[PDB]
Length: 307
Ligand SMILES: Cc1c2[nH]c(c1CCC(=O)O)/C=c1\[nH]/c(c(C)c1CCC(=O)O)=C\c1[nH]c(c(S(=O)(=O)O)c1C)/C=c1\[nH]/c(c(S(=O)(=O)O)c1C)=C\2
Ligand SMILES: [Mg+2]
Image (cartoon, rainbow, N blue to C red; front, side, top):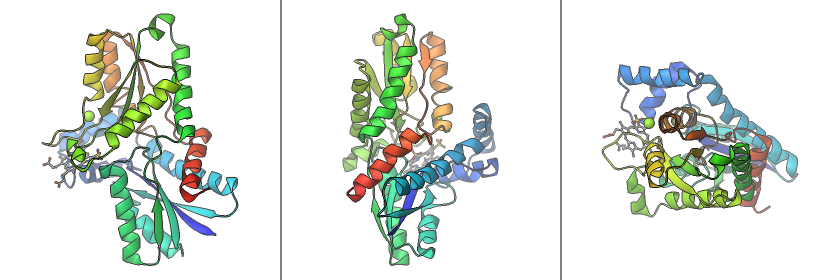
């Protein structure tokens, strides 16, 4: 049995040549002004370049198809990447599947929390393009933050981080678990996105044994509408002022890979804030394409299919 494996993600530019069109796409067609563009470029430079980041999704999708075809023998999976904000787009991935003769696919988004703006939008764009082309069906994973193998990944890293600490810090530490902020209007549709982030943080804090943790949001866009808050920078400060913590540990659980939203908005922006206040900054390794994470994903996909 052959099945397409449609792996979807937000996307990151493969080359600097694409930073401009990437950002224009995110800004819903509004082209960056030259100084904004330069600012962006400088950020990617500071984190060591854009090229490494794109490759991680490629390796994630490839490892997942491989481990999927390794662990069972009734389905042969073939992976297709479809990205929201850069080529190959979701629609081009479905088009390729159809060309290769695929009639049934399973899709998964590389974002463990369901939202209307992210997961649902991707799943719908995929299904609508399958329907336009005819004779291809897609069953879509909606959320997987609660998969135990995925909780275990983050719990072990948090445990290792607290274990590595000075004794002084362990007893005066704060866990901040976060994901990408979205327009506050999502709550008009009862979007469970904020609740699922709360549940993630609890699952991970409790598995790690952590009584003190908070949920924050990051990497918000600039629009006239309110976005989900508090932002991690304001939360880190409010927390250092209701209780004066000495170490802050950041688990960007909404992100699966090293990209700008982590390497910059956490390791720079939040680290600017901890350094200032002389609390310590910790941020454990992102899952990227480590075996333990890909196994969790394979399990999510098989569970979805009824195995
Ligand atoms: C400048 C701009 C941005 N975003 C928009 C504008 C122009 C509209 C206006 O402000 O009047 C527009 C939208 N972004 C949206 C939505 C639903 C709109 C309205 C579209 C319309 O005009 O109908 C959603 C949205 N946006 C972003 C995401 S997320 O990454 O998935 O979280 C999502 C779901 C991301 C961003 N949007 C941004 C920026 S940035 O300030 O960094 O340049 C970012 C990082 C900026
Ligand atoms: Mg920002």
